[PDB]
Length: 83
Length: 128
Length: 97
Image 1 (cartoon, chains in turn cyan, yellow, brown):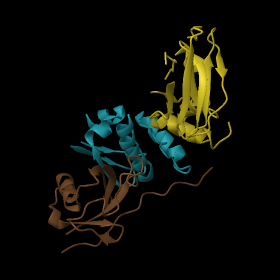
Image 2 (tube, each protein chain N blue to C red):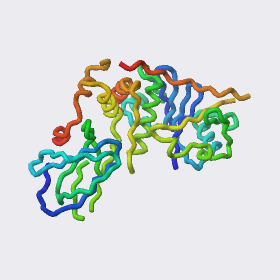
Image 3 (cartoon, rainbow over the protein chains, first blue to last red):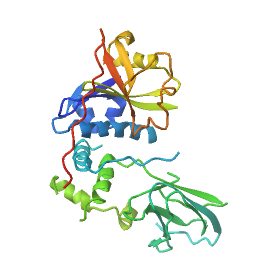
Image 4 (spheres, each protein chain N blue to C red):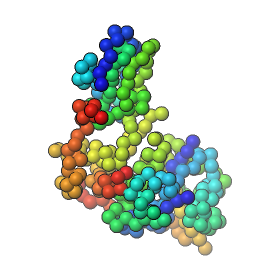
């Protein structure tokens, strides 16, 4: 079971329901597609990568990488969704 | 929160399983934090402490919070292994981390200006 | 070993995992559960290279250590006559302040 998270630029990110439910914001926006008007795809791919990273590691944990150019936007995205 | 002055020695290895320079922090008998010398990432250090003492560890440049055997490490009776790992930070904090580290103390909401300025702090976490 | 993949085509991107032992054809079965298209109407790529249904993801270079949770390998998806491989790039970030 999956959900579709669509970014601001049309890109359609399909991820497992349980991964998306980590975000409490998305659980509301599902209660199943979610449209993100302020989140472009280069930010929302990272969010999806974070879901997987978070679900797998919650051994030794690796650093979650964040490029500098996407850092601010991703911060706003993370701030809004609370993830 | 204070080390229990047991005087029962306790043999401990500070294992650094993180990509951060670890800063070990001993909570002396009055609860004040005492900073030990740092472990480069992936390096270890056999160290001499005592049953009932209180250790926590941080990134040593940013004071980000690390795990030890997954928050507070107390040497117990025997050596003992203190495995210092990255936590699974929130995505928000992780971005606060990256941003903090690329900008001296910008286009974001006012609530985020404060988040960026609410540095991780040892005295802070302790009350918690 | 689990490999973590983005399966991508046009402006579609599925995030999923598989075992390193599992097969291309078995991955096509996963796509079918999601995008509802049978494997025979699916082609799978690692870059430009058409992948064979019988080969394992590992053979095809999707290893637990390259295909990571926080950094997942990309598998190209083509639908069917068969279209060409098309993956729309993600948006490009602004300039650094």
